[PDB]
Length: 230
Length: 231
Ligand SMILES: Cc1ccc(Cc2cc(=O)n3c(c2[NH+](C)C)SC[C@H]3C(=O)O)c2ccccc12
Ligand SMILES: Cc1ccc(Cc2cc(=O)n3c(c2[NH+](C)C)SC[C@H]3C(=O)O)c2ccccc12
Ligand code: NA
Ligand code: NA
Image 1 (tube, rainbow over the protein chains, first blue to last red):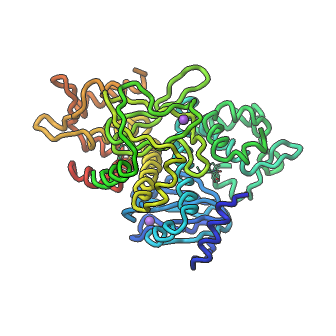
Image 2 (image 1 turned 180 degrees about the vertical axis):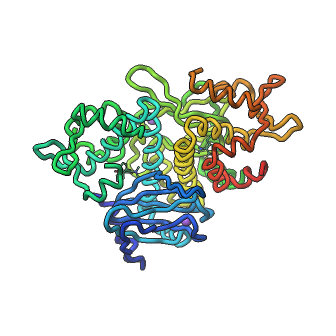
Image 3 (image 1 turned 90 degrees about the vertical axis):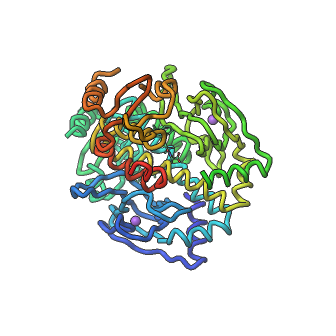
């Protein structure tokens, strides 16, 4: 599956760093801490959020294990943004590292330096591809792109199409007014199907057509997974 | 800058040389199988993409000093079918093949770090732009771009904050859809930015900060020195 992550997991463990369980609605890091962290999210699903003074809560970015999320800059160790990383799966397993300690240990392994660098690269190109799909096709591009990524990562073929294999609690979190206008177009056009309390994708090519740049991103960033359905 | 001067030293020390590029040249392109690390030392560029048609998309602006990598650092393959186009009259850039580069980061965690921090800056820029648009729609995006322009190129004068860029470069950043037009009218109405004497002037910065709140925070956390100039 992800050998660079498994290698990184061991490097952490054989350097003193131990996995921490977190449970849903827990913040692995938060916007009010004076200390920033490098998070190696080894398993589970999280969301990055921003809580404005209004108290309105903004969902910015999803992440699944294995990945690295850093709440501060590696050089200055100060915040990259007033963010929280909330667990949305039932549990998540993460290794929590003070940014300053991380610097040391990326020194002694070119290979693990590269691994973490590469995940920032994938984030950068992800946002650019989402931006592009939204410039081309609006919210449709956005939702199709979200569904395309769900299909690639969590899809399993079944008779009613490509089922999305996330726990139901997890699915409601991810969203399963303006968004509504469109989901119906898809329910009705049988791109997706909500049957027997599960979500099914019946027309992968439509998703691909309106999220072309995220499709490309996934080919270039996760070719293993992209092939499984192309 | 300082940390970028540091990194430029490091490159020239190891044999890499600046090259000039001129408006409308591509420093790297989306069809070249070879990928590069670009240390853009001076000038203004845009990242672009094409779709099947021939339809140019402007995705992201960069100014020197900055680093722009067209391939992944481990696999060396493309991060996206992108071009980096010059939009200032000249741009100075150090071009580094990704393979040739990979040893060099290996030998200098200080310098590795400077490049790592630049990706982090990009990631959080994109998120903060997204946050602003989710709050305020097109107006948040428009004010956010004018906010950054002001911070980076703006000089305080009695006629307001002058954008110290030439009208050429200002058009390449765009200075006529109906939705945009209403916003422009609202801003050109409020005198938020005023064209005066073949120049561009910002007279309500509070407004910009008001509708681009998260990009404002981004600049504070990422470019504090420059942010404090106008705060
Ligand atoms: C529904 C949904 C959409 C997008 C993301 C973000 C995401 C997914 C993904 O598979 N990968 C990345 C991202 N971003 C961090 C760019 S980076 C490369 C790859 C990976 O994790 O190996 C979702 C993430 C989790 C759950 C649902 C997502
Ligand atoms: C008008 C305008 C908006 C945005 C950008 C992008 C940009 C500007 C900037 O000052 N910085 C960055 C970016 N992005 C690459 C995130 S990264 C940190 C900082 C820096 O250059 O050190 C513009 C860039 C050039 C010209 C105009 C811009
Ligand atoms: Na924090
Ligand atoms: Na290229």
